[PDB]
Amino acid sequence: MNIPRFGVKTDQEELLAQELENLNKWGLNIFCVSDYAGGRSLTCIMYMIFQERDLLKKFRIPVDTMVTYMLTLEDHYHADVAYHNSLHAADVLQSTHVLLATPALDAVFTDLEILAALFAAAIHDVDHPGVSNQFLINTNSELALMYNDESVLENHHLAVGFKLLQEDNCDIFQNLSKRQRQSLRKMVIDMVLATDMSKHMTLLADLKTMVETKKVTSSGVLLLDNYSDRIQVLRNMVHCADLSNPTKPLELYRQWTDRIMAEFFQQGDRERERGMEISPMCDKHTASVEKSQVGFIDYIVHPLWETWADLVHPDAQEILDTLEDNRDWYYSAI
Ligand SMILES: O=C(O)c1ccc(-c2cc3cccnc3c(-c3cccc([N+](=O)[O-])c3)n2)cc1
Ligand SMILES: [Mg+2]
Ligand SMILES: [Zn+2]
């Protein structure tokens, strides 16, 4: 097969090249990347991030195998879902790619731990049906039964992400050793399960505790001596990336917000149709986009990021400021 310059076919290679100069920046505009990448934002951004970090050479990942898996992974995100489609995956991946390069964590993680984190981010919402875990539980769906109503979607994302490695020429980990494959899998399972919003409060509580006894070197670089601390940082890193929409430039944040509300509202219309209790913020007849974001930032997003900023101080001060600015805008927009 053919491997394009930026991993995917494009009729606007120059505009795409232009946007990709921001690959390692929080400011990257994934929406434009998607437009130029013909909708293959995940395959493109992932291809570029792996080249950027020299991961193909580092783990002896055949390039055609990488692109085949990525195309397959992206193909398994639902285009008919407003928010949880491949664009969200590409964004969380790209965001994680940036957070991994934070000064406070320089030289902290191995290439394998880095590989695991990016893979986790890329597959964290694959095959998402566009409805919450509770909806699946309330409808007695096959998935909820399969996973005992516990982290239903998250368990499914993991099962799919790993299963797709078995389609023709899709095993990107074929050349890793057995111990590396098992370590990677353990870390990935840990990170994706941590994206289940019902674990948010506990996660944040444990993160604050960790920040309390935070260890640093002379340069100000975090000191993570044991696996426990490294994976805890990685769990929270992916979680933050998953909830980074409010920390991005207002122009992008607003687009992300319209997508999530559209997905929520459709779940609500369906719950109404089936005579089900309408989930929080899913009733378009009463829910407010602006009101919801202010609350979301006030009680979920700002507390999380404020703690993250604390952990890698002062690396995320700018991100925090933007979040507060966006909070101000939505509040005044009410
Ligand atoms: O169960 C899940 O897997 C899940 C649930 C909610 C969100 C989510 C994403 C947002 C992205 C951008 C702005 N808002 C998002 C919100 C959200 C929007 C308004 C209010 C709240 N909230 O928690 O109050 C949350 N929720 C993602 C995943
Ligand atoms: Mg999810
Ligand atoms: Zn997500």
Image (spheres, rainbow, N blue to C red):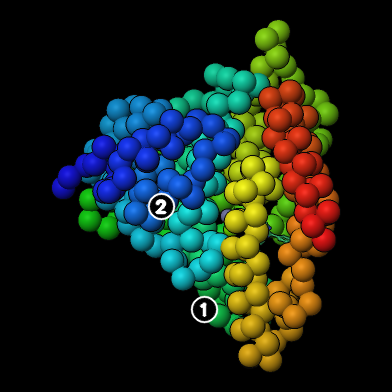
Mark 2 element type = helix
Q: Is residue 11 visible?
A: yes
Residue reaching furthest to the left: 1
Whole-percent x and y of residue 215?
74, 19
User: Residue at (31%, 45%) from the top-left corner?
Assistant: 12
- Residue in the foreground of this view, choosing between 312 and 281: 281
Tell me: 303 left or right of 262: right
Which quadrant, please, contains the C terminus? bottom right
Q: Residues within 10 Å of mark 2 (few under 14, many from 20)?
A: some
| Three-letter code, disc 2 | Asp
User: Residue at point 28% right, 32% down?
Assistant: 60
Residue at 58 percent across and 19 percent down: it is 106
Q: Is residue 79 left or right of residue 99?
A: left
What secondary structure is marked by label 1? helix
* Residue corresponding to mark 1: 142
The x and y percentages for residue 56 are: 31, 32
* CA gap, disc 2 and disc 1: 35 Å
Q: Is tag 2's residue or tag 1's residue first in the polypeptide sequence? A: 2
Ligand 3 is located in which of the four quadrants? Answer: bottom right
Per the image, the residue denoted by label 2 is: 35
Pinpoint residue 333: horizontal percent, then vertical percent: 79, 57
Disc sitting over residue 17 in the figure: none
Asked if the residue at tag 1 contacts the one at tag 2, i.e. Cβ–Cβ closer than 8 Å, the answer is no
Q: Could you classify mark 1 by the number of other residues whose Cα lies within 10 Å: few (under 14), some (14-19), or many (20 or more)?
A: few
Three-letter amino acid code at disc 1?
Glu
Please give left or right for residue 210 compared with residue 2 in the image. right
Which of the 4 image quadrants contains residue 5? top left
Q: Residue pushed farthest top?
A: 218
Q: Nearer the viewer, residue 241 or 297?
A: 297
Please say whether residue 163 is visible from this viewpoint.
Answer: no
Q: Nearer the viewer, residue 151 or 31?
A: 31
